[PDB]
Image: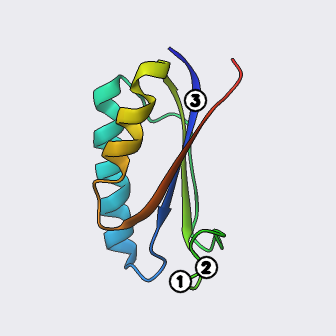
Amino acid sequence: SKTFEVNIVLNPNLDQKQLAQAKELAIKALKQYGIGVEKIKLIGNAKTVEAVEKLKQGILLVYQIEAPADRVNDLARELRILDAVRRVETTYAAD
């Protein structure tokens, strides 16, 4: 496994409860890849460029994770399973 970053974009019109639930569910997905919960960031007023096209802002939820390259596609898929989520992007990071 290598250092890896995932970026989840959520509808900014969601309740704090709904967002919290989406976060928990996202974690429950990630855990299935052996991913922990040690380094997590969220910006609740993020104006994601891929969101503001239709939305007001576009909430930026980020996990700093460790995963093999093979599971990158699977990570992206599961993170998109939610209705709260509008978009997921991925990238590799240095160790």
Q: Which residue is mark 1?
A: 55
User: Looking at the picture, does residue 49 appear above or below residue 22?
Assistant: below
Q: Which residue is mark 3?
A: 4
Q: Quadrant of the C terminus?
A: top right
What residue lies at 45% left-to-right and 30% top-to-bottom? Answer: 72
What residue lies at 40% left-to-right and 74% top-to-bottom? Answer: 16
Structural crowding at the residue carrying mark 3, measured as other residues with C-alpha within 10 Å and reported as few (<14), some (14–19) or many (≥20):
some
| Front-most of residues 51 and 11 | 51
Q: Is residue 61 left or right of residue 93?
A: left
Q: Residue furthest top?
A: 1
| Front-most of residues 51 and 12 | 51
Q: Which residue is mark 2?
A: 52
Residue 35 figure quarter: top left
Give residue 20's position: percent from left, percent from top. 36, 63
Structural crowding at the residue carrying mark 1, measured as other residues with C-alpha within 10 Å and reported as few (<14), some (14–19) or many (≥20):
some
Q: Is residue 36 left or right of residue 54?
A: left
Residue type of the residue flagged with mark 2: Val
Q: Residue furthest right?
A: 94
Structural crowding at the residue carrying mark 2, measured as other residues with C-alpha within 10 Å and reported as few (<14), some (14–19) or many (≥20):
few
Q: Is residue 7 left or right of residue 31?
A: right
Residue type of the residue flagged with mark 3: Phe
| Front-most of residues 55 and 34 | 55
Label 2's element? Answer: loop
Label 3's element? Answer: strand
**Distance between the alpha carbons at the discs numbered 3 and 1:** 28 Å
Please report whichever mark, 2 or 3, sits nearer to the chain's N-terminal start.
3
